[PDB]
Amino acid sequence: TDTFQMFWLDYCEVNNTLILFGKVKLKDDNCVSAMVQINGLCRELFFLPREGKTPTDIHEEIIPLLMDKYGLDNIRAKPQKMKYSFELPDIPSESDYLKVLLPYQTPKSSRDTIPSDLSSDTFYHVFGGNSNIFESFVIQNRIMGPCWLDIKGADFNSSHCAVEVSVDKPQNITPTTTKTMPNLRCLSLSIQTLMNPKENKQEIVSITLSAYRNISLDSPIPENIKPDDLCTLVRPPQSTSFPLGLAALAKQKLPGRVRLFNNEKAMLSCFCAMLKVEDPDVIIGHRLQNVYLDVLAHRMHDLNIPTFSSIGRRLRRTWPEKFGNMNHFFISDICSGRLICDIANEMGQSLTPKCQSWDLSEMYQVTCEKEHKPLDIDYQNPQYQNDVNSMTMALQENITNCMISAEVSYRIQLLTLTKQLTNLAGNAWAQTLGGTRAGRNEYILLHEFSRNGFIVPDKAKYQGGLVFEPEKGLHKNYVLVMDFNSLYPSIIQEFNICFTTVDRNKEDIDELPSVPPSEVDQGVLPRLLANLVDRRREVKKVMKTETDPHKRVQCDIRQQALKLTANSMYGCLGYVNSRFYAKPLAMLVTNKGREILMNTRQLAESMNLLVVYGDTNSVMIDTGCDNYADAIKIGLGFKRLVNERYRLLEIDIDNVFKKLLLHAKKKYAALTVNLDKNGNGTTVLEVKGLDMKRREFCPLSRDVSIHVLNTILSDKDPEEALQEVYDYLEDIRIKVETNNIRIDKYKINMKLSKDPKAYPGGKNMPAVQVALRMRKAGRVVKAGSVITFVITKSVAERAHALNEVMIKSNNLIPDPQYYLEKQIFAPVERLLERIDSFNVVRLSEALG
DNA sequence: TGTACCCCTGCCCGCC
Ligand SMILES: Nc1nc2c(ncn2[C@H]2C[C@H](O)[C@@H](COP(=O)(O)OP(=O)(O)OP(=O)(O)O)O2)c(=O)[nH]1
């Protein structure tokens, strides 16, 4: 009747007011975009009186000063007992502050914040004087992520949205308890570009728009869901005219609508109009955030498009004057309103760790198990300004790419997972989709603390885990790997480490503090971490009884995502730029960790058990058993003995290795025993740290390492197994020298963290030279890029891009000398070093 | 206005 109900998704700050973008059900319950403009929000300032003065003394003093300063008729202010438990010195654990409410929008001095160090005769500190509008709203009104909102007193008369409402009382908006959510209008994008040798900038040739008007995150997303619409927007690449027969052939072979334009300006103008109309909640894509959104923005800026703001939901008539590495924030604000669901950004990458480059094709293969052979489209080639079939081919590649981005997006549950994490943290959905962890920690703490009458802080360096020196070599007996479930998170709870409970010297953050006595009640941090580990426990419970393989994978991501979250809770204690940075606390967590790992080793030593290796939270035990169950007895026995030492913290049997080959620290190969339904036990090769597992080692090298390990660890006569390996390698030598191997098996990946320019000794680095050639060719390469290349027949002077090599026309052949020495010999030598009766010279001979 | 979990351990490259 009078209660206006909106489901918020994103926000934006403007003119000292807060704006929420969301979805609304009308009388027929149909869902449309809406934009609320919340006014009358205030900052909760807290003045701290000196020893001898009281909140009353302060009020008498500043309330008139502030009224004059900001020209206010009246200012709400009351005394309030608040607790401080953070790194500042000279702040009492609890005091009577004068809580003052200073509206963000004031008649005068609207943006003159009160400095926290402001001193006076009555007070000496002032908390919460710089807090940001969004924070103040979400905290005061207890909003915990994307949720339904009851908004009373909605003014409709006083954006690219259907509805536009404004409220003058923040108190009017209140969260509902409804856990169901609207359907989301998703619009996947795919943009093809070409570089201009004139200005050295990237221009847009085509854009594909795959709409999915009803995506419900309540129920699961059906696989391969077909879009409710598909539309491509093509521009000429070289000349102003396409090739005769493009339209006809397009509607004959290409899926969905295809509309041709005369120049770019026109194409983008249509694109913007289309966004405004479709008005989607989420924008799917691959490398949107870090490449294509940036390009799109600059082009619209250069071509002087008026409807550029269409990308977002806020109507901007003018471009941010500072536009032209701040483009990050700028673009995020312009997109304010529509969630950017990039599957290849940090958030996406964290859900798909099995990838080495996160190329769209690789991501498709990994997450969907479907193979797609990518096509290198270079619109610089006149092949596309003349041949018509080439053009239709490129467009088709772009359609498939857009479709793949969307599918993978739904497959990895990017939207469902991020939303849930956002509701857990109480921050914004967009921010979580960006791939933040400091933000989700910051906000979960902001809420938990504020809810319990705590003052929140205004807006290597220590020793880590313990890693034992391994018993480097092979262990033919059954080995046990005992692991501590969520070591650090569990430690926090065990010894009750928290901002509120741990005594620490705030004059020296490098001074190790000490666990609090059992008398002290459980703090904030252990409580939240408690809930986190509970959630991961429940998800791993469901994963153990899931029939579908696809759903089980989907659960594995979910549990290691909640794992990342809880671990991040700890990390942010040691994150210098964390709002809740507490070096001493982190220090203490790692400390008790090491202590516990020692005690775990010693406990085994006393039982005359062999501790062959350990890393942070695990220990490996050579039991001297020839069978599984006999080791398992010693395992469960040792388990019972350590669990008695701790209240919450508990060790368990992680894996069992029929045979273990320790190479170094953090590197080893072993044979895991996996039990089946009918008690059947099988063997699987597990590897850690070894060269084969790195991206700088080609697929050939990987296969070689895997075979060598399989036979070496296989129950075969030691000298006979060695023989089998030598022979295998003699054969590989011939295959590589003659060139009887597919070039794809030679490919090497290496991510440049810096720009290829910022590499002084880059002349030696092959990946750098390759990135330089790529850029010259017109390919977008930048910090974070992953470069795939091959050494052909100085090493760096002979390294070329993979795609350039797979072009027979270029006649590029891999250098067998390099790959035999570095890619095959080096790793196998490191694989077999500590193995009995291994001969290094015999190996060197078998190759060169 | 303006982001970004922690530390541990090897392998390149160069130099003292
Ligand atoms: N800050 C931070 N700490 C981590 C991270 N990964 C691991 N750690 C630390 C904290 C963990 O408690 C400890 C154990 O690491 P593990 O990889 O074995 O996973 P964890 O023990 O947390 O869970 P699990 O054994 O799989 O049940 O190492 C991380 O990504 N960030």
Image: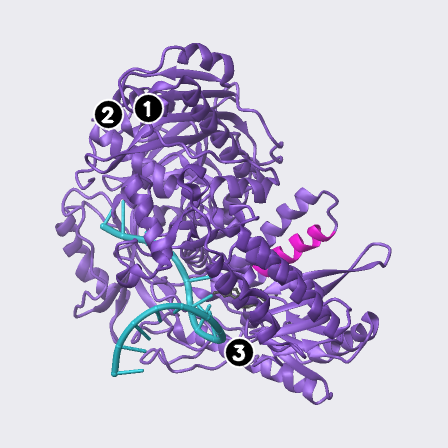
Q: Is residue A223 above or below residue A690?
A: above
Q: Image point 72% across, 53% down: which residue?
A: A544
**Image coordinates for residue A339, horizontal then vertical, percent:** 42, 37
Q: Is disc 3 placed on a helix, strand or loop?
A: loop
* Residue type at numbered disc 3: Leu
List the single residue furthest toward the right.
A678
Residue under disc 2 on the same chain as residue under disc 3: yes
* Residue type at numbered disc 2: Ile
Q: Which of the pair A285/A384 is nearer the observer?
A: A384
Q: Which labelled disc corresponds to residue A272?
A: 1
Q: Which labelled disc corresponds to residue A466?
A: 3
Query: In which quarter of the view is residue A337 placed?
Result: top left
Colour scheme in the image?
by chain
Contact, CB < 8 Å: mark 2 with mark 3?
no
Q: CA distance from mark 2 to mark 3?
A: 58 Å
Overall secondary structure of the magenta section: helix
Left or right: A242 as drawn, with respect to A360:
left
N-terminal-most mark, 1 or 3: 1
Q: Which residues are magenta?
A: A532-544
| Residue A535 falls inside the magenta stretch | yes
Left or right: A313 as drawn, with respect to A595:
left
Q: Is residue A158 above or below residue A843?
A: above
Q: Give the residue number, with chain letter if any, for mark 2.
A: A305
**Image coordinates for residue A749, horizontal then vertical, percent:** 45, 53
**Mark 2, chain letter?**
A
